[PDB]
């Protein structure tokens, strides 16, 4: 599923991401835009053989099991394919674990390089929340 901007913002707000660990909703929408272009089915292979999955491009090296990343962890205790669902619950719940691990949203390269330090509130402007 390819979300609309305000549609995704509302779904993330309902799942408790607004101000989670101090990160306002616009941060999460901005991250999703540049990680996946709002597409739950996005996948991208990393040079180490791991793969990033879903709207927030969660990496199989640490967070999910895809059966093809030897020596990796599954810290969210989920198959990586669950992160491609049109229902973003699994992605949101796993992202809550990632953001709590000590590095905040710097875990998402696109957030650090394209959202951090910008007017992220613009990403939820106009949305009925
Ligand atoms: Cl915001
Ligand atoms: Cl594996
Ligand atoms: Cl933080
Ligand atoms: Na894994």
Image: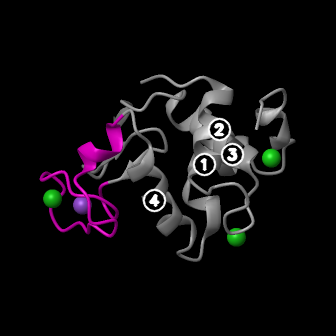
Q: How far from the left and from the top, in percent, is residue 71? A: 18, 68
Horizontal placement of 7 versus 42: left or right?
right
Work out which residue is located at the far right of the displayed protein and give it: 119
The yes-or-no answer for disc 4 within 8 Å of ligand 4 is no
Circle 1/circle 3 CB separation < 8 Å: no
Distance from disc 3 to disc 2, alpha carbons, whole Å, reads 24 Å
Of callouts 3 and 4, the N-terminal one? 4
Read off the residue under disc 3. Answer: 113
Q: Nearer the viewer, residue 31 or 3?
A: 3
Of callouts 1 and 3, the N-terminal one? 1
Of callouts 3 and 2, the N-terminal one? 2
Circle 2/circle 1 CB separation < 8 Å: yes
Q: Which mark is residue 93?
A: 4
Q: Which callout, 2 or 4, points to the residue nearer the camera?
A: 2
Distance from disc 4 to disc 1, alpha carbons, whole Å, reads 12 Å
Read off the residue under disc 1. Answer: 14
Read off the residue under disc 2. Answer: 10
């Amino acid at each position: 599923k390819v979300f609309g901007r305000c549609e995704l913002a509302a779904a993330m707000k309902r799942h408790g991401l607004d101000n989670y660990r101090g990160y306002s909703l616009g941060n999460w929408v901005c991250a999703a835009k540049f990680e996946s272009n709002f597409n739950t089915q996005a996948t991208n292979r990393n040079t180490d053989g791991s793969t990033d999955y879903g709207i927030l491009q969660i990496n199989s090296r640490w967070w999910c099991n895809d059966g093809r990343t030897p020596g990796s962890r599954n810290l969210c205790n989920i198959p990586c394919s669950a992160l491609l669902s049109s229902d973003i619950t699994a992605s949101v719940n796993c992202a809550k674990k990632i953001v709590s691990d000590g590095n905040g949203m710097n875990a998402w390269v696109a957030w650090r390089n394209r959202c951090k330090g910008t007017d992220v509130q613009a990403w939820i402007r106009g949305c009925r929340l």
